[PDB]
Amino acid sequence: GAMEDITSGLKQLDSTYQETNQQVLKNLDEIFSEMGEEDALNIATAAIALRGDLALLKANFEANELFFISEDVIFKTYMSSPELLLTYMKINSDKVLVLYCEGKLKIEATAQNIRERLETSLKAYQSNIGGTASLITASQTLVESLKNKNFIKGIRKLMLAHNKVFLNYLEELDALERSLEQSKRQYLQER
Ligand SMILES: [Cl-]
Image (cartoon, rainbow, N blue to C red; front, top):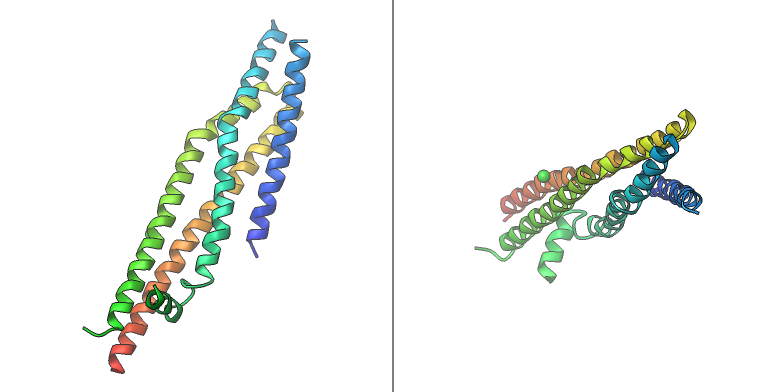
C-alpha cells in the first residue's frame, strides 16, 4: 500500500544518486584531464562524500527496505494474531498458559529486534547525513544548488517514511500484546 510508495521513493533516489555521481566523476575527469581551483576542490570533496557518507546512507535505506520485506512476512503470519502466535509457539500450571507465556515472550523479542534495527538506522542517518552539505558547496549555479537541495529533501523524506514504518511495527506489537492478554483472560475465564 504505502510501501510501494517507499520502494519507489528509494528507486528514484538511487537514480538521482547514480546520475549525480556520474556527473561528478565526469567533472573530475575533465578537471584532471583560483575560483576554478576552489570549485575543483569542492567537486573532489563531493566525489568523496558520494563514495563514502552517502553510499552509507544508501546502504542503510537498502537494508531497511529488505527488512521491511522479511519482517512484513513475520507480521502477516505468526505475529498477525494471538491465535496464530500461540499456534506458532505450540509448534515451536496449565499447558496453554505456558503457550501464552511463549507468545508474549516472542512479541517482546520481536519488538526488541525492531528497536535495534531502528536504532541502527537512526545512527547511520545521523552519522552520514552531514556529507550531503558537500553537494550544495560543490554546486556551481543556483540551479544546480536547487537540484542538489531537492535531492537532499528527498533523502530526508524517505528517512521520515522509514522511521514511520519501524514505529508502526512497534505500535502494532503493542496492540497485539493488549489483544493477547484479553484473549488470555477470556481463556482463563472459560476454563
Ligand atoms: Cl517500543
